[PDB]
Image 1 (cartoon, rainbow, N blue to C red):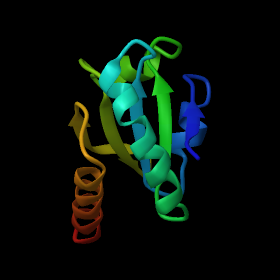
Image 2: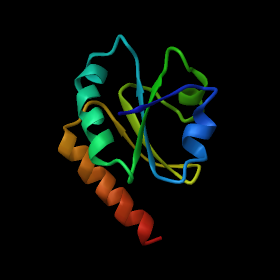
Image 3: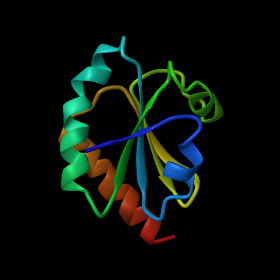
Length: 111
């Protein structure tokens, strides 16, 4: 299952994580956000012990999206050792997100 992260818990759940985190920015009023919501509960379990998948609600926790320049939702951002390394805007098939995390993982290993 996915980790629900707030402004108060973001630095402990995400920036101090010992693993890549996929942070998903959403709002209860966005439709695409509800379209990809099942896909990320599947990736949460498929990628357990490899990638944490976090959900941040931009209406309850405004500071974290402000700090990273979110302009639309869904916005998915990958974090690695406290730093934001990549992002994807808009709804996206489950397999495109895997391809993106595979290439994020390859690129991080070669730097």
